Each structure stands twice: as structure tokens, then as C-alpha cells.
Image (cartoon, rainbow, N blue to C red):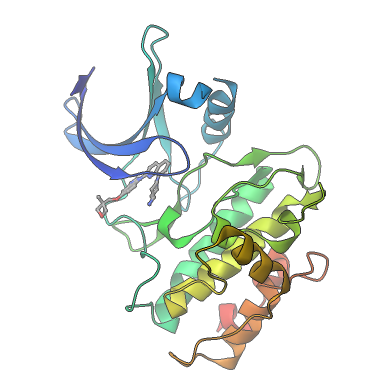
Length: 263
Ligand SMILES: CC1(COc2ccc3c(c2)ncn3-c2ccc3cccc(N4CCC(N)CC4)c3n2)COC1
């Protein structure tokens, strides 16, 4: 499959919308990641162009760079070319091979930087999870998939829609009654779920039945698996990130000063 200078190869991810394919670029003799979208499949335009707008203003070592967009109005397919991050996702969940505490800290430091940057740029990511965190050749993670991200005006996003990955959704986004909830806190909750996954290899709240998953997220006290044992300070940080109450939940400026993070 040829598309200008790019030859499209195998699928390397799904994501919130469309698919991601490896692409060889004949002009500079290296590889890219190409997100491929069907206009007809998205109908059943503007949300895509808002994602492009977001991506265009972003430039940080812990966020995946958009290189260009190929958008022929006579074709159904829209192509978004990104930098390729060689090693791919930090982990698949579940896994029996979780990260050590030291590896988790290292990636979690990158995650903090990335998220701090996004929030500064007035973007709520909305889909933070291990499979969206790509390990670069330098060993550092980069945040990917802005498919469900929101841009806001003023100091925080005021949100009412429920999107993202169900196991990573904050309890305040799961009410039966339409509610309004703050966006920065949602990303903190998902960072917490992610950190739990990093060290345990499974999510904190799990069920095959979507309604029971929601029920657990809202009403089941957080439990730690029997293995591996983790340090008291990491338990503390995870507990404060997974605070069901978005008002008392730890904020990113506090996370950066947490003893687990800074030791
Ligand atoms: C083939 C291997 C390499 O994997 C990969 C995967 C995605 C890779 C990658 C290397 N460099 C970049 N990206 C991207 C780029 C843009 C994306 C825009 C939207 C969504 C994506 N993703 C992120 C990962 C998720 N699991 C699926 C959706 C995106 N990914 C796996 O080990 C080698």
C-alpha cells in the first residue's frame, strides 16, 4: 500500500478510533506510525480536526509527535503520521510480569512530566493507561492516543460525557444522573490506575459486566493484591490518586512532591 512517499505495512495498534500502521518513508529512509481513519466509519469530520488541532500545538519529549496529516477530500481515508516509538507499549494488562518498583517510578516520572505539560496546554488526555504509554529508544515513555482528549478554556475542563477505557474511568464520571466533573482529576485517577497496573499487572477494579465494573469503581474500597509486596510510600501515593472524592484527590503538584516520587 503506497501513499505518496510512505509504504504502509502491518497494523501495530488499534486505539480509540481507527488503527495504527507501520509506515516506511522512502524519502528519509525510516519508519513512522500512521493512524488511519475512515470518514464513512466515523460518521456512523470535526472531532478529528479538533484532535489534529490539539496535536499540532504539542511538543514535549513525553508526548508522541504528529509529523503530518494526509487528507484527500476525494478519499474516505484520512492519515495522521506520527513519530514511531520503537519498543511500543510499556506493558499489556493483565500480565504476570509486572514492573519492579524502580522501573515503575522511572516511567511514572515521565508520565508526570507529560501530563503536567498537557494540562498546562489545557488538554485533558482522557485515556491514560499502560497500553497508551510507548517506550522510546532512550528508555523514556511517550503518551499516545489523543482520540478522546478535550481542550478547555480557563483553569480546568468542566465535563459531562463519559469516554475513555472503562477500567480507567473515575467514579465521578460514572453517575446515572448527568453530572459535571473536573477534567484534571480524571487524568489523575487514570494515572493512579496506571501506576497500580505497573506494579501489580492488573487493574484495581475489574468485572466482565460493565454495570458491575461501574459499581465497583464507585463503591468498592481499593484493595491491594497479596503479591507482589510494595512499599508503604507507594501504597500511600496510589491510595491518594484513587481517592473516590475528586475534591480531596491528590493533584499533580502534590504528586510531584510525594516521597515515593522524589526518593
Ligand atoms: C509494533 C511495536 C510498536 O508499537 C507501537 C504502537 C503504536 C505506536 C508506536 C509503536 N509508535 C507510535 N505509535 C502510535 C502513534 C500514534 C498513535 C495514535 C493513536 C493511537 C496509538 N496507539 C498507541 C498504542 C496503543 N496500544 C494503540 C494505539 C498511536 N500509537 C509493538 O512493539 C513493536
